[PDB]
Image (spheres, helix red, strand yellow):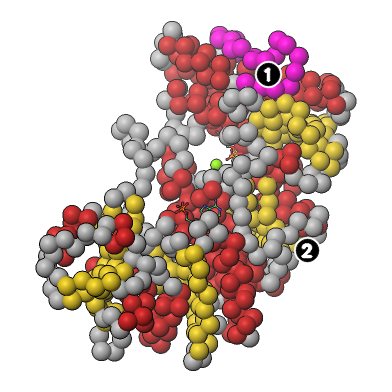
Amino acid sequence: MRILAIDTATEACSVALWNDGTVNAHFELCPREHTQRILPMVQDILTTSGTSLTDINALAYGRGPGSFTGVRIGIGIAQGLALGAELPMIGVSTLMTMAQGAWRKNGATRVLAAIDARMGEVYWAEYQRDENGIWHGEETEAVLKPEIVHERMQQLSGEWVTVGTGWQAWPDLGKESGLVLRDGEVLLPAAEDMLPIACQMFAEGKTVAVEHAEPVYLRNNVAWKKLPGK
Amino acid sequence: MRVLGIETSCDETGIAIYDDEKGLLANQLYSQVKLHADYGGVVPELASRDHVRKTVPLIQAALKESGLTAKDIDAVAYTAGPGLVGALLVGATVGRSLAFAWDVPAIPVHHMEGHLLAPMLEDNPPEFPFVALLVSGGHTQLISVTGIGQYELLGESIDDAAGEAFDKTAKLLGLDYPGGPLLSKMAAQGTAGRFVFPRPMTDRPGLDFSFSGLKTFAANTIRDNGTDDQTRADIARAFEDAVVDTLMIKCKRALDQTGFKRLVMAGGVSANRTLRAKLAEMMKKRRGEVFYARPEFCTDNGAMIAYAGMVRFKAGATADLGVSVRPRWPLAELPA
Ligand SMILES: Nc1ncnc2c1ncn2[C@@H]1O[C@H](COP(=O)(O)OP(=O)(O)O)[C@@H](O)[C@H]1O
Ligand SMILES: Nc1ncnc2c1ncn2[C@@H]1O[C@H](COP(=O)(O)OP(=O)(O)O)[C@@H](O)[C@H]1O
Ligand SMILES: [Mg+2]
């Protein structure tokens, strides 16, 4: 199969192509530049791998959580691409992608992902990889205050690694948890790490048509106050 | 030739297809007004989220409506500004990336040039030169238009735009946001002349506008008078007549100054029925012509974007692979 992945949910922009047994990937920090870099990266990957958009079997996109604007950039681009080339789409959690990154970098199999969500919160997940390489823990995804994370960590056990910008903003996040924590060495998701997840999803038929691709924001209380009485 | 047009500048998602032989082949529009009404203003985060929900589906509906397929589209145009960054980004990312996948040119469009050119979508369109009165939610400008992208600013608002003025006064009359259209309907119920509002900046020569003082006058009038339905109709009428006289007086002066015989009106306020009637009456006495779009193309829509897209494509305004938006983008800065 051939799978194209795109991500812009955080400070990083990345594109990566699973091309029948090899990976061709780009990754950089693009603060302020995501929309200037993302299509040129896609173009470059397709050209250097000698594939065209209509040879692709699915388009994997970073679904969120993360920067609201970023997440929308990602799914915007991914949607026009998928609409344009009639590609099925595969939404991948930015939290799960960082877990996979940790597995890639250092063999980690139990990951505490925390993204700095601002407003003194983090986007949180507990991911654990089984013997078949499947990541369990998607039901744990949430936007949480640090003191609630702390409570949650006291209900966990064993050894975990930490990933994501949540841990930099709040390095004492696991204080008095009772867990052995090590640095997972991943701050940001990479499209390259969406690929193994998406390939698996494709093989199992977990794709959606472009009109059903949705972002996962996790924080949905985002309005100011309603007028008196509604 | 056919152009797909995409409009997501504020709180309307609009998609249209414009064919230069056969005309408008599709026009899809979703308005978010119910989402924002609860808040008394457009909430950017929510506007942005709802553009995502709507853009792709309304594109699919547009193609189905027109009975066309990808290969029948020659270019994809999208509103790049001015407007809300968050909203603009949704339509620009989808559009630019769609253009990339279809391997067709992508045409970024200036939202107010869309408004300006909407009258070109009707029969008997205006020939150059003309004075343009752009009168929208956040814009109120008099422009001398000598050709595509030759826009000389002649007058503009120094405070509130005419649309804001309508909405702000409507809110004082207890109407839901945006209340301009409803204010206009209430006004049809009013006794002409029972109240009399100033025509600001009509006592000295010049072409700029101000409308803020008009809200003040409305609010004081709503205070010193009864809160029955009629009295509110009468205030709505006085407010409307004054804005319309002001716009008229100023259009007269710009026609005088330019010597031009053609007056083109555009933006959401150009849907206002009193305004349309008064400018038409004026252009008849002057022995010139007035032009405007159908009421549904005065307010934000995709048709104007597909049309202006076609014009800009033919003028060579194609984008590279980057996507950019310009939330503030003066019309005078567009090239010819
Ligand atoms: N007006 C814009 N035009 C193009 N890209 C933008 C714009 N605003 C934001 N972005 C992209 O989205 C990213 C996330 O924006 P934001 O969440 O506001 O975080 P920050 O501004 O702190 O980078 C930006 O880094 C930028 O690359
Ligand atoms: N019949 C009308 N009379 C007066 N104002 C109107 C009427 N119809 C729409 N409007 C006003 O036009 C504005 C919307 O203008 P439009 O060009 O659609 O949006 P934008 O300002 O977002 O480009 C609002 O201020 C709205 O209240
Ligand atoms: Mg609007």
Expressed as whole percent of the image width and height from the top left, the position of residue B183 reads 52, 26
Q: Nearer the viewer, residue A188 or B180?
A: A188
Expressed as whole percent of the image width and height from the top left, the position of residue B259 reads 88, 25
Chain of the residue where label 2 is placed in the rendered structure: B
Q: Which residues are magenta?
A: B192-210
Expressed as whole percent of the image width and height from the top left, the position of residue B4 reads 67, 60
Q: Nearer the viewer, residue B68 or A64?
A: A64
In which quarter of the view is residue B272 placed?
A: top right
Residue drawn 55% across and 59% down?
A: A33
The residue to which callout 1 is attached is B245
A190 vs B308, left or right, is left
On whether disc 1 and disc 2 are found on a single subunit, the reply is yes
Expressed as whole percent of the image width and height from the top left, the position of residue B310 reads 75, 56
Q: Please name the amino acid that badge 1 sits on.
A: Asp
User: How far apart are the two marked residues, 1 and 2, measured between alpha carbons?
Assistant: 42 Å
Residue drawn 73% across and 11% down?
A: B204
User: Which type of secondary structure does the marked residue at label 2 adopt?
Assistant: loop
Asked if the residues shown at circle 1 and circle 2 are in contact, with their CB atoms under 8 angstroms apart, the answer is no
- Taking the magenta stretch, the answer to whether it contains residue B207 is yes
Determine whether the beta carbon of the residue marked 2 sits less than 8 angstroms from the nearest atom of ligand 2. no
How packed mark 1 is, by other alpha carbons closer than 10 Å (few <14, some 14-19, many 20 or more), is: some
How packed mark 2 is, by other alpha carbons closer than 10 Å (few <14, some 14-19, many 20 or more), is: few
B312 vs A165, left or right, is right
Residue drawn 34% across and 52% down?
A: A118
Residue drawn 62% across and 76% down?
A: A44
> Is A8 above or below relative to A25?
above
Q: Quadrant of the N terminus of chain B?
A: bottom right
In which quarter of the view is residue B273 placed?
A: top right
The residue to which callout 2 is attached is B1
- Taking the magenta stretch, the answer to whether it contains residue B116 is no
